[PDB]
Image: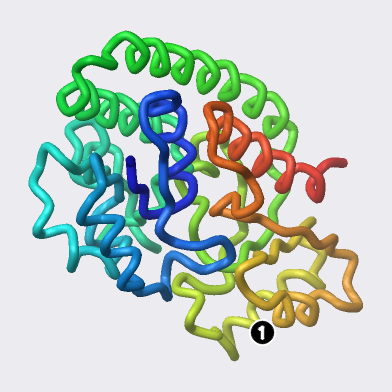
Amino acid sequence: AVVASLKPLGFIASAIADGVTDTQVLLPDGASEHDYSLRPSDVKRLQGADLVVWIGPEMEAFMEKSVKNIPDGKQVTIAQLADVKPLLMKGADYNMHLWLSPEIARASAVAIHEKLVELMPQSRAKLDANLKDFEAQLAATDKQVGNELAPLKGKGYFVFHDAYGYYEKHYGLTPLGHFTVNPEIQPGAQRLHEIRTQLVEQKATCVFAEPQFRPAVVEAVARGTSVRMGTLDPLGTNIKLGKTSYSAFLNQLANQYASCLKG
């Protein structure tokens, strides 16, 4: 099997290795990328994976550990890829929420495909063809999203937790800023003040919760005000692995942003 660390890395691998081997996500639905640690049975899945896909040690900390035993032909480490490295952003030490960069996704699909062809050479036929389709969906989605999000350029909003840099920069969104960075921090207390003042001084159209964290803090700093409220799910927790899953992720996310920000 192809064992992906996070669900949207699954979405990608599931497209490339469709019909060739199954894909498996380690980080379960509704857990957060910051704050997991590998089950014994999750390490089994890694030890006997055909191919392992993850970002890199600055992101999925919890699995740097087990990935040192795995050799280079049996894994794809997306933060240290040829075409990705050059376009890593800074953390306002780089932002690693890469799985939302279509350019990076592309580069990842490529590298996955390469390694699978190597390991499973009698499936080259299908693999080559799965990839072609991916590149096509992905391209055609990047177009539709672009259009959907284009009218939200300018509209300022706030997000819980800083995950969306890559996506936001690429489609030209206009975030006023984030509540946290690591969302195991609260954050309080001045942070929450600076947001409040910004929201009541008109200035912001939407504020965005997340499903893997209590919206609790976001209602508040908003109640009373003319700010609308929504949610963003950066792990597409409610999307099934499949060919068209990663293109669905981006569309969903676009719709999440837009469903609140439209006007």
Q: Name the residue: 68% across, 30% down.
A: 150
Quadrant in the rendering for residue 107: top left
* On screen, residue 223 above or below 55: below
- Percent position of residue 208, x then y: 70, 62
Q: Nearer the viewer, residue 34 or 87?
A: 34
Across and down, in percent, residue 72 comes to 10, 42
Horizontal side of residue 204 vs 120, given as left or right = right
* Local SS, label 1: helix
Q: Is residue 170 above or below residue 225?
A: above
Q: Nearer the viewer, residue 165 or 239?
A: 239
54 w.r.t. 207: above or below: above
Q: Position of residue 148 (x, y in %)?
A: 72, 29
- How many circles with numbers are drawn on the protein? 1
- Residue at which label 1 appears: 193
Residue 242 position by quadrant: top right
Q: Position of residue 103 (x, y in %)?
A: 40, 30
Pick out the residue farthest to the bottom. 189
Which image quarter: residue 29?
A: bottom right
Q: Please state if 246 lies on the left or on the right of 99 as rendered.
A: right
Q: If the image is split into quadrants, where does the C terminus sit?
A: top right
Q: Residue at point 58% right, 82% down?
A: 191
Residue type, numbered disc 1:
His
Q: Nearer the viewer, residue 49 or 26?
A: 49
Whether 196 is drawn above or below 58: the answer is below
User: Which residue does the image show at 41% across and 53% down from the upper left?
Assistant: 97
User: What is the quadrant of the N terminus in the image?
Assistant: top left
